[PDB]
Length: 117
Ligand SMILES: C[C@@H]1CC(=O)Nc2cc3cc(c2N1)/C=C/CCCN1CCCc2ccc(cc21)OC[C@@H]1CN(CCO1)C3=O
Image (cartoon, rainbow, N blue to C red; front, side, top):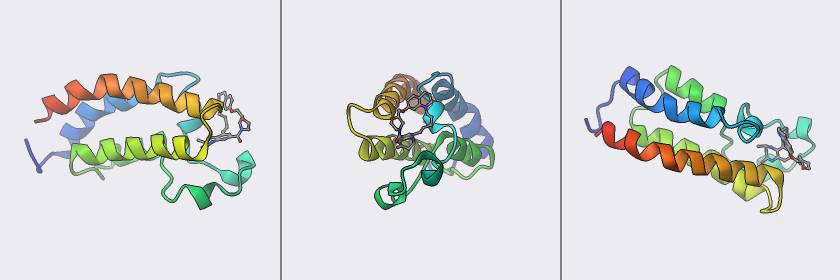
């Protein structure tokens, strides 16, 4: 309905959109796990990205019912996108990978949101 959404209702409706992102290979690969700046040799990552976000964290929040409203899920997805757009330059591979994920999410999310009311 509105405001009051059940955790299982949200998960069953929103999880396919997240799975659509996972299916993108290799585009989802940089976003499957939280960023490890020291592992990746980018020590200034947390200085630029104030609020890290990735697919595993979003999936965890859906499975544990940490989203009360479907729009909170969408916000985390765009936070993950913006982190990659902000930290990386437009010519970089991780930037282009992110833009492919955004395209997939933009084409899948509209019907799902309308079915949730
Ligand atoms: C989201 C997180 C934080 C961020 O915002 N930017 C990044 C930045 C960087 C790495 C990651 C990175 N990702 C992560 C790499 C691990 C494997 C990711 N895949 C898997 C599939 C093939 C693949 C191909 C190219 C690729 C990455 C990549 O990148 C090209 C490199 C990576 N270089 C150095 C020069 O360019 C980074 O400095």
